[PDB]
Length: 135
Length: 128
Length: 127
Ligand SMILES: *[C@@H]1O[C@H](CO)[C@@H](O)[C@H](O)[C@H]1NC(C)=O
Image (cartoon, rainbow over all chains, first blue to last red; front, side):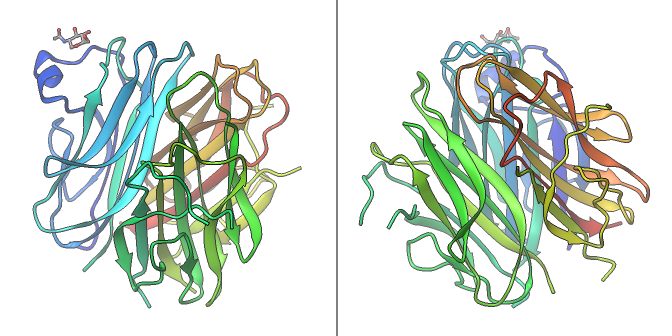
């Protein structure tokens, strides 16, 4: 209803599943907040419970930054915003962006690795979201 | 009044138009219409705490300062190393009055090749 | 009233706790100790975001958001040659009354200082 919020973090440097390599969906294992449980089980897809304005924020951190990576915030399979990183030799680098989106009942919001790979594991990556107000 | 929010994106790599103000053509969210027509200015409709967030993406060292009534409040920097793209990002909460104007100014550098994928967001957290 | 909790601070000109002298917003006065410290007044979901600016070029820094002396999220800037690189991250947290949230310089020393570093947070909704 009025209180919907999720907060996830990848607490581990493990490689992606070969199921996750296909779908190109970035998943998060450690869930710090899930109010209304609309952020589902390690699929890392948010299901809008009702109509309203929602906030979204992500940071995709990588240990290996050789090849460029592009992360796109998806809405029902269509990209909304994008973040860019890679082509670096650094300690750790984050591809980060945030946006507010008007959602209708049942929309799906998730992160897709449009380009690059998650070799060496993404760790300390974050994905947050909450309902600002329903409309 | 109670529910105020905006959200905009630079959807094309087009060169800037003629004031040193970074505008965004694609508006996802505008609740209350307090974010003006295809430019960067948000006008506070009531006293309260407002959230603001911006990610200005480029393709030289540019400084983006979040302006409030003509003075800078926070600043972001994007030193151009050997990269395809780079973002100057920051965010803050500000206490604002009815009539205050928050917008993004490009203090240093220029945006050529476009500032595509740059975002700007903001909403009223609670009134006062 | 009790449902309105928000703070935001910048850094202008020990336990490795980063501080932000200029306080833009403090509603409820629950951010104190001349830094990014903040005690939750009530149980609920709180938002947090921070940008720690790596001023000097050749350094590497790591900033960890702390919850009662334990890291929750980490931000990284360094091993590069770019001036004023931001170690940034954000998270929502479930917290109870008395929980302390602050920023710790986990690795490195902010050289050239840190300036235009921001640290803000607010109560999304109580529980
Ligand atoms: C998924 O792709 C990454 C990057 O190539 C690889 O390291 C990982 O092993 C792949 N997953 C599986 C299950 O092989």
